[PDB]
View 1: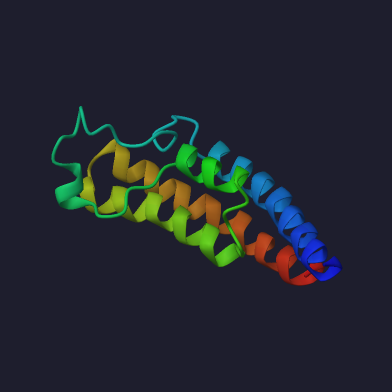
View 2: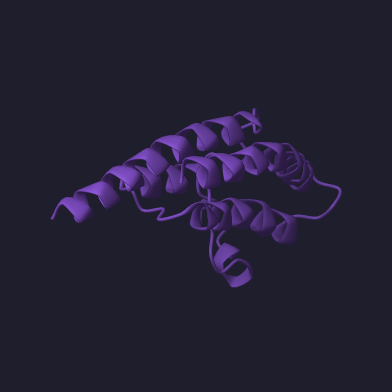
Length: 121
């Protein structure tokens, strides 16, 4: 149907906007602490601690399959990146601190993304 196509075009345009959001958030992680999944070879107990691991590469895979239906879903995954790190790692660590800085800086980006998503529809 034409209605299904129109819905697909809206999903495609959301995907474009989320790709730009993702790039902007990842630039706030110049150390690349959040770039890839935590390695279970190197942290063999990780899944005992963290039930839903997340990282920027995994988000990018979902994005390119147009797997985010709305901004809320994408924000959920970004929040997992931060939240998982702040649980596993102590306050005095470079990992925890990197997550705090990512959260704070990403807040700015996400605030305007929400406006754009509501605005363009």
